[PDB]
Amino acid sequence: ARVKRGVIARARHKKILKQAKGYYGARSRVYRVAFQAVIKAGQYAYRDRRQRKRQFRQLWIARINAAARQNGISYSKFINGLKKASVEIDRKILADIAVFDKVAFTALVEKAKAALA
Amino acid sequence: MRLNTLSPAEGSKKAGKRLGRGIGSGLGKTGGRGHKGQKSRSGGGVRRGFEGGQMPLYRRLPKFGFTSRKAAITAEVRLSDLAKVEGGVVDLNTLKAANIIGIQIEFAKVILAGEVTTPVTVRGLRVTKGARAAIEAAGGKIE
Amino acid sequence: PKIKTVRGAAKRFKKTGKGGFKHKHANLRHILTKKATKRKRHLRPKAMVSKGDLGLVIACLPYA
Amino acid sequence: MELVLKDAQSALTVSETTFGRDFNEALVHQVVVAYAAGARQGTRAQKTRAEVTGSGKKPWRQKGTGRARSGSIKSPIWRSGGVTFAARPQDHSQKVNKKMYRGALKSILSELVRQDRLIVVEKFSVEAPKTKLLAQKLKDMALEDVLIITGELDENLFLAARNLHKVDVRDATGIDPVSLIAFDKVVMTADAVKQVEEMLA
RNA sequence: AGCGGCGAGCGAACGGGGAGCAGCCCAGAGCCUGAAUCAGUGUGUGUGUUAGUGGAAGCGUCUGGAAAGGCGCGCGAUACAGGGUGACAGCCCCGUACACAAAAAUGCACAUGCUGUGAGCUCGAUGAGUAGGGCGGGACACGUGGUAUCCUGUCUGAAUAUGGGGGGACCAUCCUCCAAGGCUAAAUACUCCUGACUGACCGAUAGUGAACCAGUACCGUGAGGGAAAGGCGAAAAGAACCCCGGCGAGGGGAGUGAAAAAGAACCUGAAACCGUGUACGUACAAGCAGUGGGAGCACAGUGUGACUGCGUACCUUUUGUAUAAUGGGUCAGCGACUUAUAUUCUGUAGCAAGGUUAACCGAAUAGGGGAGCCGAAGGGAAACCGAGUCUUAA
């Protein structure tokens, strides 16, 4: 029972070169380079599923901070004023309000500025 | 019950370690052998009783005794074998006819090892003190 | 092929009933005037092979 | 148990140990595999690095040239030299215990009366040694893939199934694991089931 | 069991189961006197081998380039082993099962006739520079060790059946045998070679080194080494003729064909690698080239990806590597925990105080074969004793 392995090594190699589309140069064509391109690209994909949840929370907080300061309060006092008022909206939606319905944000700032001070 | 329906018992066939076949098998890149030493080489591994070069235990200790050459020609007859001797007379040569002792045996002893039931006749053998008290307890005469 | 018994081990050990090995004690060959009679008295019975040594002995005695 | 005949309707007596045992699948799988492995003609071999035709000359020197170190043109890393663990002709037979072989056959014959694939006849014989008559033999019997097991040395019947592919004639002493399973009906003459009951005790 | 720097290791016999099983001559003279033998040679028979002969049965139909395929309906089969045929054939072919055949030359038996050896009976005879020994070696499982036995280079040297050898130093008994002459079938080992037949053997980097004009081309003074290289199609029907060209090479038609993207540099035609066309991006932007976010654009979700956050390959080896330590130009193919036997343990299965056979026989995976092996008893160095036993006067 000799086993030739040309068919399943072709398929195993083809599966990895298919995951390497768009890569530069020999990282799309050569298996040895494209294998560790794909293994590194899965490593980054694991890491940046963590960093995506930080980078967006970074982006919301920077926008609520700007939109609070147009209404005359900082991000810290707005978030403290919302918690003392028991408002439980998260920062994804607080930033969504801040660009799309600004008059629904100036009401939120007022409800924070009131119950803070 | 066709040829494509018969299965082994569960756990009757373990697979078999296939060494050096990748990361997922848990046996790749060393073959379960660890890193570079004598024992990870092909054919490497020291002989039996090697201790390093410390004097081995079978050479640290004294030889004792001798081989008897009479223990090779003696055997023990359990009382379980007094019913199979085909005639009720336990000679030396009738224990061999029933394949109890062995053809090169010159001395047999009958020891108390289980349930003599029948009228038996031990002739020309040795019996112990327990076996004599059991053969006569079933109605047997020892010569 | 059959496994060859280490024949020098087959003169040092004898297998007992529950499976272990009896052996003569060392230190009772020569140089005995200086040894105490109590110490020489305790080397005269046969001892059992220790726990850690037993794997080295059954390796040596496969037909014990 | 009881084994009803094909048409005389007078069921001969068998011992229930041989035809009414519980089925043991691990026992029958082992004896159907050892039959299958003992049919292997283990005749193959390849060449090791010793046996490949070549010289033991070291191809280049050990040092100096910037090529990987080699010492034989017949090493298995090299093309056209050396299978690493090359085959030899071997014996693929297995040992079966007699009480495992007889326990399997007693468990197959017990299962053949469960799935109604044992039919006992009292005589199965054919007048002329002609395949045409036996081809008729089982149409009325309604058989196409069958194993006939007889007790006598019928050579007229034996030739008449030598060309029919799905029909096998035996002599009640060479019935085996794989033959009692790979046929759809097993048909036994009444003199033959007397002998098969005997040898399986 | 023993041997053994009693280390590494070496490793029997006796006895038992089997295969196969024949014993005979000369050292010698008589009666009898070819008296079976065992050979060779020659007719004769039986049987192979070396050429061979006969073989048995299917047509319509649809797809298709072509039917052996499909659907329909028959027939042979002691033959449905295999192969070929335009795709997969029991019934087309070659065969196969079966039944047969030999001028001539040979293998084997037998029948033997004719030649060579040479019986049976009476008696005697009973293998000397040998056995043994001293010395030195070697062989025996046995390394000179307490060491038998065998062989003999050297030096010696018997007894002659009322005598001699051996029985593991040696001796006495008493068992057994008769060295110093020779022949001897089968069971056994092997395969350059021939015939069939088979394969959980290979399928062109494999399998022989060699599927092919291969021990060749080549290399070496030489001994020697030693390659690579299979496939058009069903059939050459292997491309008439016309064009461009140099009366080229190559190409474009035309044609053959099912197919020429089957055109001979010929099945399939992967990947590296190299082009052309198209979409998008790109000429103020720094780094493992991805990843997360993400516009714009082009298509019918896909493609691209400006800008942007994070981000120093892989392996190996290490206390520790982006490491400026190792390894790799890349692709494709091959490339490394096997096999035999023994042993122990776990799983599992069968049978259990029993369980199993080995060789071999065998209608061959059956059945027979229980020689054995392991277990049911152990203590003791051993004799021995024995559910106890050793220790010790206890």
Image: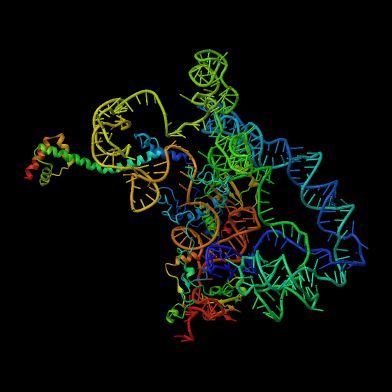
Q: How is the image coloured?
A: rainbow
Left or right placement of residue E42 versus residue C43 in this view: right
Question: Which quadrant is home to the C terminus of chain D?
Answer: bottom right
Q: Nearest the camera: D71 or E273?
A: D71
**Horizontal and vertical percent for residue E49?**
73, 43
Residue drawn 22% across the image and 41% down it: A55
Quarter assignment of residue E340: bottom right
Q: Is residue E189 left or right of residue C53?
A: right
- Look at the picture and state if E330 lies above or below B96: above
Front position in the image: A6 or B97: A6
User: Does the image show residue D36?
Assistant: yes
Observer-nearest of E224 and A62: E224
- Taking the image as drawn, is residue B86 in sight? no
Looking at the picture, tell me which residue is in the foreground, E343 or D78.
D78
Query: In the image, residue E37 lies at what x, y percent?
Result: 82, 58
Q: Name the residue at 38% across, 40% down.
A: A35
Location of residue E274 with respect to E360 vertically, above or below: above
Location of residue E392 in the rendering, given as x and y in whole percent from the top left corner: 48, 84
Q: Where is residue B30 in the image (x, y as percent from the top left)?
A: 42, 51
